[PDB]
Image (tube, coloured by chain):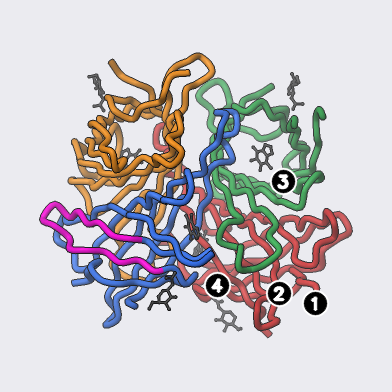
Chain colours: A orange, B blue, C green, D red
Amino acid sequence: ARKCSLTGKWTNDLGSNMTIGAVNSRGEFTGTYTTAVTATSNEIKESPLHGTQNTINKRTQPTFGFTVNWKFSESTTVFTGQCFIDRNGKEVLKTMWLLRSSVNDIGDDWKATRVGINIFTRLR
Amino acid sequence: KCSLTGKWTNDLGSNMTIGAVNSRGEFTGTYTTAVNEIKESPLHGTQNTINKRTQPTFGFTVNWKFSESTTVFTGQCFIDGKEVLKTMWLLRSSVNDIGDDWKATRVGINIFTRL
Amino acid sequence: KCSLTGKWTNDLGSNMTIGAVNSRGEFTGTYTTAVNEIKESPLHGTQNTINKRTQPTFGFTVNWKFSESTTVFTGQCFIDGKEVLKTMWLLRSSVNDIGDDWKATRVGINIFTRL
Amino acid sequence: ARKCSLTGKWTNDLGSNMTIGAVNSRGEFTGTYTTAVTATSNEIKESPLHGTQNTINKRTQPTFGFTVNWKFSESTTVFTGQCFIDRNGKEVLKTMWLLRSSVNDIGDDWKATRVGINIFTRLR
Ligand SMILES: *[C@@H]1O[C@H](CO)[C@@H](O)[C@H](O)[C@H]1NC(C)=O
Ligand SMILES: *[C@@H]1O[C@H](CO)[C@@H](O)[C@H](O)[C@H]1NC(C)=O
Ligand SMILES: *[C@@H]1O[C@H](CO)[C@@H](O)[C@H](O)[C@H]1NC(C)=O
Ligand SMILES: *[C@@H]1O[C@H](CO)[C@@H](O)[C@H](O)[C@H]1NC(C)=O
Ligand SMILES: Cn1c(=O)c2[nH]cnc2n(C)c1=O
Ligand SMILES: Cn1c(=O)c2[nH]cnc2n(C)c1=O
Ligand SMILES: Cn1c(=O)c2[nH]cnc2n(C)c1=O
Ligand SMILES: Cn1c(=O)c2[nH]cnc2n(C)c1=O
């Protein structure tokens, strides 16, 4: 079977794009995230990301996580998922995310986290 | 200014130490859980520097060294005069078959204070 | 007006039928998954009636009859001209010891269309 | 050991209160939710809830779920968790929730779900 590789340019269901560079032997990678929409009335852009792929047992379809450090807001998003070979033999990232808003008071902390999915496929 | 650097412990008794935060907001650390005895896994993340908030949001990934899983944590560094990290996490399990993907993600909270 | 009453199927191939929605917005139904063959569990929930929106939010609980677990789903009934339910769910597993509570909750999405 | 029972008045970490009535033999219950804060600039109140407790194997510490049908907004929250006897012998509900906002466009669906926890203890 193919190995599923994180390295490449990706697009998701919402029209956002993402690039991920080479993964080092420690499983670390950097990338960029170019977002389609926004929960702010601020314009979007490219924002950097950093994360790791799990290399335990050197699975062909590894789990990974990354953090997006939004450059156009005070928020942070983390993504986590797995690099699968799909039924049709394509690479697919199946991910879920938490979007953390900045709040001014610790008493608003409870409503500062949104959750959802994103499915990435390779954009050539 | 609530800062991520230092030694932390959470509501479950796990420990975490985080190094210096660089100008791009990036930091690395080690996450410590007990089952055997104690396990140590690297973590890497960033804090948000937009508006240079005294109470910044942040994120990090734990690359578990004892399983195939990955966890990401995100939240906000609060300063009352004690510092507290309020976080939520997603724990992604490895599945073999994409048909099992639906059940591979767990979610929860952790609250960290200085150890 | 996007309506919850009827027969639905999701992206995983599970089926769901929901009865009439009463004046308090309450409804009951049956949720159908395949493993054996097919299982049937009751569900109960409400749709939100504030402002009598054409595309209302809603929630429901599935009381699984084949395990000790419970799932809740919440989301919004959209009308494009096809009706689509966009939902997220939490699947709560039973643990024996409160010390295991942290890992008892999974999260995901389901999208339902008319069957 | 005690059985953990849903029936009663409860308070959580945020200061919200909740009542749950008798649970019927089908595991069904009704209740009310009186909330401390809000993600809206609307005032709070009492809102009804309905849900079920799992009775498979008649566990002493059952899982359950319920839906809160907010009367002061277009949103809906679902809660799910387990009724534990804690280390100190008290009943505790350990729950997690999804708060679904109403959006006007299906294209905003992605940011319409927030997530968090709530810990309930009996208020006498
Ligand atoms: C994603 O990449 C495609 C191919 O260049 C580009 O046309 C499209 O507009 C991109 N989407 C965003 C939101 O940048
Ligand atoms: C966490 O912190 C302290 C170290 O001061 C120790 O009591 C405890 O055993 C540690 N737990 C670990 C290493 O998981
Ligand atoms: C769901 O819907 C249709 C019934 O028309 C059927 O093809 C499929 O097998 C059903 N799946 C179940 C019952 O889980
Ligand atoms: C919860 O109940 C207590 C006891 O009556 C009451 O004083 C308190 O204000 C309630 N909290 C809310 C938000 O209603
Ligand atoms: C996950 N996610 C998105 O999918 C998105 N699209 C636009 N902003 C976005 N943000 C901030 C985000 O966190
Ligand atoms: C969040 N979290 C924990 O709190 C934990 N405790 C033990 N393993 C753990 N893992 C893998 C995890 O992701
Ligand atoms: C959401 N969900 C599912 O999609 C599913 N499929 C099979 N069991 C399932 N359970 C228990 C569940 O909660
Ligand atoms: C979970 N939750 C709360 O804890 C809360 N507090 C105030 N509104 C609230 N809402 C709408 C809510 O869904």
Residue B50 in magenta? no
Image: magenta residue range: B15-30
Position of residue C31 measured from the top left corner of the image (x, y, whole percent):
74, 37
Packing grade of label 4 (10 A; few <14, some 14-19, many >=20) is some
Does ligand 7 reach within 8 Å of label 3's beta carbon? yes
Q: Amino acid at mark 1?
A: Arg
Q: Are marks 4 and 3 on the same chain?
A: no
Q: Amino acid at mark 4?
A: Ser
Q: Kindly identify which chain the residue marked by label 3 belongs to.
A: C
Q: Which residue is mark 3?
A: C62
Q: Which residue is mark 4?
A: D16
User: In this view of the protein, which residue sits in the foreground, C4 or A90?
Assistant: A90
Which residue appears at 68% of the width and 55% of the height? D65
Position of residue B113 measured from the top left corner of the image (x, y, whole percent):
36, 75
The CA distance from mark 4 to mark 3 is 25 Å
Residue lying at the far bottom of the rendered structure: D124
Do the CB atoms of the residues marked 2 and 1 lie less than 8 Å apart? yes
Q: Please state which of the two labelled residues, at mark 1 or mark 4, is closer to the viewer.
A: 1
The CA distance from mark 2 to mark 4 is 21 Å
Q: Which mark is residue D85?
A: 2
